Image (cartoon, coloured by chain):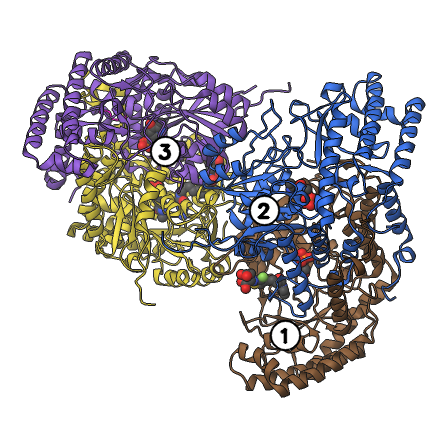
Chain colours: A yellow, B purple, C brown, D blue
């Protein structure tokens, strides 16, 4: 045993599962707004020997030796991070060790807030993320709502936009120590300047969580939250198209006559290690670094520009076929479809599209509160990486409308949701039209190229 | 732009760094106890298209669709995890989604405790890990100490062993809710039956953090903590020789007048991992973990684990018979806790001189040095070099390279006082820089001849 | 030394201070809405031998012996408490051991809530009490805001009333586990039914803190919060006219087919003792019992009826002289005067009236946020006990208008507040007119009878 | 209705209860260590018009006006409090507003600690008070245990004394922020210098809760904790013989390179009392406290306190020489901790038979009874009866009344098994009810002859 045997030969059971997944990604129409296809260059670094190095600590301040080159790798990742977002190293630092987006956000709260201090984020059904604090009416669900006291703010249901007015009203009463500007299911641009004004008024930190839009921010195709945010967290995948990891950006420098300094760097870095994490995943850090260099490229500006065009084309196509869009349209990479007008819930449309290899996710619509959410969240980044263009997404909307039509017919043939799901498998004619739509979807999808390796 | 361009063509500056790190890995003698060299099969799955799937939730109960393949990969990783540790799927479940060792522990505390509930772990300078609760005297350092109230139990300074008697005394008073039986710098087996007695008395949870010894437990080579513990957390690297990830083992079924009082661990542990703490699972890490878990079920891994112990005893005996004391005496696992206090050098000086000759170790506070900037000795591990087909004679040669290094360190220390004057000495003085560059050339020539798991060039 | 020597003979220094205070109460016009003059019968029990008995525990479940009669005293106090508020002993229990109003409220939070659980009360400048949670924008001030997380609700400044609408909006977002219905500076009737609806919607306990209005509730001259509240706390003084102590009323009995029981009694009683308090003050409990029997009397119904008439007469007199009243008037025992129209702040009017033996307290007016609050809180219970009637309070308003006029003249003669206060003492003519007003106030006040002892 | 009607005319049913309680107080032998009989002067101020003044805030910094007289009464109570304990007003301040002993402690924790900060007090069954932190094994009982994390230190079971050695060991591990040197059932002096050493080591606050011994400290009759403690809380009754209230003593001035690091206790303590925890002060209690504090400055109180000790030693020696063991051996303060385990009766049975003959004591868990429903012995105190002009011969007579009671209890126990069968026995059996009613008649005749502080009829 050398440890150099191929995965094909060493573990054939796992190799056949890698290939069944690679085929599923190649043949499916991937519309999950948070999914992207990582590049082969980054995957090489992700599955490299850097997994073998323990480098607890930070460059130059490591706890062990032999970190000579992984220090260069981490520092290179930090420089490429600041450059991909046009940041001044005198005004901004970055931590590249958060294992993912959720550990990044928990590190910020741990670094700046005391246990049970107050956090405000967009409510979960309104488009926020779990890590922004989420409690049901019966249970603290997000750990952010266990170690800290979270109170959500809401969309204005009439407009589909964040109710910056009600946020200002509630933040003055709730007195939060940190407010989160960032979304998972939101088709619009967050007014970071209005956020920073509410935060300055109530003496709170503004955290911009730009996981979904980071790739767009790096290409300068949408306004940068760095202009108004004290702290910026992000996933290194999604629109950034790297390996799954996280980043924390923070301010440095100067925040009677004396100059008050920014005090984020030491608290943030301490919260990641020693407080929360252990040994950094240097393989992820390296893969993140390759993607961050890919993001300063002109090809990323045109890809991100295409992501916007493709989402608008998908939105425009959806409106023409008679669909409703939460907040009317989109200014970023995703589209919030409201299917309650057309007579179908998102849960039904989710399963039907899943059976025809169209992966999307149900989404609560404003004024809906469920097991049967009324909407669908459709994303452009994944297919746009596969060189999709506007006409390609208009065809994607065609396949979706076919899928919705199939769901409408099954809805009249069924009572409850489980009757609906059971019908898509046992009924012969429904099974047939699904197979016909699925085959046309996969034939259309396989022709497009796919980032990464060819075999796995 | 296709995204299928090779890393060599796409990012040369990066590619050079992956090669330089591969070279330093190859040329060096890795003796850090937590290190290991991963198999090419696992790194193939680590850098797979599995990174491109969001599968929040759990198999059969996920939030997005299209997770049919990753559902089987997670379920496979679960079954391979139970089989690797000889567990009945009726008495044990496992969560394979923790991102690393530290997240796995935080999930267990979240799952079973309320904030500020009481926790007892081995003190950090006594060989415990940060995640077991480490407050200093001025600062709560570990996040375990902030969101929970942790009091440490100590080693007996006379024996180097865990003072199981003091732990029973201080547990009756501190009334902890969970005690952690796990180490990062401890050369002996842990009396898990004695922990379970103290835990059954104060009505506490017995969590076993076998991260450093996960491989030795799977190979049935040291006693298994699963016979006494309710919850077992582990890392998937170190002795398991996998990708960086974590696991949480928990008992399911019936605990015990009345009826069947059930084990309530599973739903709480799974809920703490998601949605409480983590987001989307790292399916590419879960797959590489599964790969390495299959490798741990095979007879080659038991012979590997048995070779780790022998190289450890060989390292200990070879160190004893050259003028070194070892706290706890010998070693019953994979590492040795050397005490450089009886040779006139400290751990900080020794690892800097050893690192300068491609020999990586780490300081470790020994039972006897209140000065923790100049710690007692070093922590040296076997599992890394053992994976390069090292045997006992190769480790007695490593001890010779080490003793030759500390003696360049004993001479360099006789000519200076403070540690930075020490360090600056090792770089400029031509007579010491030459004698270092010569020992370094001989260790690189010696290590390069051995094989190396993984790819050839990165 | 027998311990039976008179205070007159044993400690003459303290005796001369008792008499200087007795004279100050006899000669002053006491307008502090929370002040009342306790009856002699209760004071006898307050300064009795019951101070000498340790009775930790509860009647029948004491931790020591010899509690044979103090058990009868505590149980008698419980029966008179339930009877004074027309409560069914099958539906209501009462704890008579809270040392005061603040320990009563802290016992409720401790009994029903976990540390850091959420509380909502009327904001402090809006008329709430400290124990309802109060944080400045810099410090947690009330211990209620330290051991639990409080968020306040506000008055509607346009109307001076509680914004029950904004409370419902914020309670749905804040998700409090207990909401407090009760005030210190509020001239209106709290809509307890609307409170109970907000509490039932967000699954919160409704605590009615009726310290200021308890005497009115016992006389059935205003609606009883017991009709809508799960828990009722109160001080045993203020409008109840007893010794300084506290009471916690709670529900008993019944809150698939099974009957869910009320679970307040054991948690409330446990929070008082063993958790929070030590040995009960049986001397206070006994004095509280005499006052509670005085409250079931027809004389208390007419006294409380007179308290309402006197406050309305004081309010009507104030309006006629050109004063503003927060929320336009009053339906209870106090009056919130807004002096910002007449050109004087409450802090100035407070000191000027204090120098003429008219004790009131400054009060923040809605839309004012200070060291110079714009209002004055005037109460009727104290003087109404001294047999004041409507024409007497109209004369009190005359003395106040004279005092305000003196403050207006000093305001033009001075710059800052400290200049104002210093002017009332050093300036000769100002000092004179104050002495003339003070003498007329005290001559008018001394003629009225005074509950309690004659000498101390 | 004037409100000046007498209680006899206004509420006869109440008045009868005040008289019945006055009679039972007069007719009985009060031996509860925390009891005492207040002076008529203090009860005159307790039931004064001072109840009718809201004086939220502090002298010079109040929120209402018209507080000129109560400002001097509070300031007098402060000066009398410092003089009574021989404190320089430059090194000590005092807050006289705590409603009782428990509120005074909670204010100190609030003032100096954050929620869930660590606290160490004597364990409750070992003689500590609830307010020092008492969690059982199923429930946080004291509010000190809910809002703060408390670990108890124990007695040495072999000596009955505070195990100061174990406390130093468990303080280095628990890292407390505040340690409480105070007792409710402990017959020895507390090595406050040894507490200050343990506190100065783990960087903790030394709070002294002298509530049970406040009078003996003021009379310079036992060593004063003010020489070693930073904060001293006390009750104003018990040995101080005042109304029910509390005090918080704190150091002000300069603590200690650089300049004058100031004592920061005062503002935090005062702020915790108001506005944090309490509302309007009980000015009638503050005045009665001041009255009793002046009485404690006088030579009659030192002779009184000295008589308390002698009656305590007389009670201890008289109990020893009749077949009783006393934990800790003797007594150096005001109470005696008897152990009825070596005589075949328990504390629950003895206090029920003694209470039935107008002799009030209390159970106390002795060092040796895990069964705490049938506690070891009784706690008996001197300060109560000493205030009735009791001397040593009168206490040796009380011991005779006690020993005659336990022997009716040893015979009643030989004829039954469980405690309720015990209790029901003492009421129906004509031969035991007669023998109880005879001993009762002799104790009432004996106690009634002694004087009684306070009023004559209520
Ligand atoms: N805008 C936005 N869109 C999306 C789309 C996907 N996500 C993330 C998916 C998780 C969010 C989530 C909401 S509810 C809930 C939960 O309690 N689920 C289990 C608990 C496990 C158990 O009890 O077995 C149950 O109670 O069923 C959750 F986990 C988001 C998001 O975060 N935001
Ligand atoms: N509606 C209503 N009316 C009234 C009228 C009187 N009261 C009660 C009086 C207290 C309320 C209070 C508000 S602010 C504050 C405070 O921080 N005061 C000191 C702190 C001490 C120090 O720092 O020396 C300072 O910061 O100046 C307070 F104490 C009330 C009430 O509770 N409600
Ligand atoms: C290494 C280790 C950890 C942490 O593992 P990470 O992957 O660095 O998070 C936790 N516990 C023990 C016992 C360990 O050895
Ligand atoms: C996806 C996301 C996260 C968390 O990312 P993970 O990798 O799943 O931890 C956090 N915030 C936002 C806005 C996200 O979209
Ligand atoms: C009696 C006592 C207390 C409590 O006094 P209370 O007036 O009942 O609150 C607190 N600590 C000690 C040491 C005591 O003896
Ligand atoms: C006066 C009051 C209190 C507290 O009473 P205290 O005796 O000062 O403790 C609590 N709540 C309200 C509404 C009050 O008016």
Give the CA distance from mark 2 to mark 3. Answer: 38 Å
Discs 1 and 3 lie in a common subunit: no
Q: Residues within 10 Å of mark 1 (few under 14, many from 20)?
A: many
Mostly what secondary structure, the magenta segment? loop
In terms of secondary structure, where does tag 2 sit? strand
Mark 2 lies on residue:
D232
Relative to residue A432, is residue C170 depicted above or below?
Answer: below
Please state if B206 lies on the left or on the right of D370 as rendered.
left
State which mark lies toward you, 1 or 3.
Answer: 1
Query: Label 3 near label 1: C-beta < 8 Å?
Result: no
In terms of secondary structure, where does tag 3 sit? helix
Mark 3 lies on residue:
B130
Q: Residue at x 60, y 58 (%)?
A: C130
Q: Is mark 1 within 8 Å of ligand 2?
A: no
Q: Is mark 2 within 8 Å of ligand 5?
A: no
Q: Is mark 3 within 8 Å of ligand 3?
A: yes
Q: Residues within 10 Å of mark 3 (few under 14, many from 20)?
A: many
Please state if D358 lies on the left or on the right of A357 as rendered.
right
Give the CA distance from mark 2 to mark 1. Answer: 37 Å
| Magenta residue check for B169 | no
- The quadrant of the rendering that contains the N terminus of chain B is top left
Please state the horizontal and vertical placement of residue C4, each as a whole percent of the image: 83, 52
Please state the horizontal and vertical placement of residue C76, each as a whole percent of the image: 84, 47
Q: Quadrant of residue A34?
A: top left
Mark 1 lies on residue:
C350
- Looking at the rendering, the stretch of residues picked out in magenta corresponds to B34-38
Q: Residue at x 77, y 21 (%)?
A: D345
Relative to residue A375, is residue C38 depicted above or below?
Answer: below
- The quadrant of the rendering that contains the C terminus of chain B is top left
In terms of secondary structure, where does tag 1 sit? helix
| Magenta residue check for B37 | yes
Nearer-the-camera pick, D248 or B22: D248
């Amino acid at each position: 045993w050398t440890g150099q045997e191929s995965l094909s030969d060493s573990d054939p059971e796992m190799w056949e599962l890698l290939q069944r997944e690679k085929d599923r990604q190649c043949r499916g129409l991937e519309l999950i707004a948070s999914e992207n296809f990582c590049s082969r260059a980054a995957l090489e670094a992700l599955g490299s020997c850097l997994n073998n190095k323990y480098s607890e600590g930070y460059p130059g301040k490591r706890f062990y030796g032999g970190a000579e080159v992984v220090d260069e790798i981490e520092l290179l990742c930090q420089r490429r991070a600041l450059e991909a977002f046009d940041l001044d190293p005198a005004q901004w630092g970055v931590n590249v060790q958060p294992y993912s987006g959720s550990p990044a956000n928990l590190a910020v709260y741990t670094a700046l807030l005391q246990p049970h201090d107050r956090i405000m984020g967009l409510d979960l059904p309104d488009g926020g993320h779990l890590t922004h604090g989420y409690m049901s009416d019966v249970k603290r669900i997000s750990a952010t709502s266990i170690f800290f006291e979270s109170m959500p703010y809401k969309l204005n249901p009439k407009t589909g936009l964040i109710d910056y007015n009600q946020l200002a009203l509630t933040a003055r009463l709730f007195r939060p120590r940190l407010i989160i500007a960032g979304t998972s299911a939101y088709a619009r641009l967050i007014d970071y300047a209005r956020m920073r004004e509410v935060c300055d008024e109530v003496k709170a930190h503004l955290l911009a969580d730009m996981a979904h839009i980071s790739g767009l921010v790096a290409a300068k195709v949408i306004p940068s939250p760095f202009k108004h945010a004290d702290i910026v967290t992000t996933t290194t995948h999604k629109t950034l198209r790297g390996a799954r990891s996280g980043l924390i950006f923070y301010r440095k420098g100067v925040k009677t006559g004396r100059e008050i300094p920014y005090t984020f760097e030491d608290r943030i870095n301490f919260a990641v290690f020693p407080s929360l994490q252990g040994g950094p995943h240097n393989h992820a850090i390296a893969a993140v670094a390759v993607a961050l260099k890919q993001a300063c490229t002109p090809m990323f500006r045109e890809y991100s520009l295409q992501v916007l065009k493709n989402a608008r084309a998908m939105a425009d196509a959806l409106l023409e076929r008679g669909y409703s869009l939460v907040s009317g349209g989109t200014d970023n990479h995703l589209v919030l479809v409201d299917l309650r007008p057309k007579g179908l819930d998102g849960a039904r449309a989710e399963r039907v599209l899943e059976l025809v290899s169209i992966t999307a996710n149900k989404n609560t619509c404003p004024g809906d509160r469920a097991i049967t959410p009324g909407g669908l969240r459709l994303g452009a980044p994944a297919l746009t990486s596969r060189q999709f263009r506007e006409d390609d997404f208009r065809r994607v909307v065609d396949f979706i409308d076919e899928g919705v039509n199939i769901g409408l017919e099954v809805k009249s043939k069924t009572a409850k949701l489980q009757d609906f799901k059971s019908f898509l498998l046992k009924d012969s004619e429904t099974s047939q039209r699904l197979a016909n739509l699925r085959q046309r979807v996969e034939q259309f999808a396989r022709a497009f190229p796919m980032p990464g390796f060819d075999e796995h």
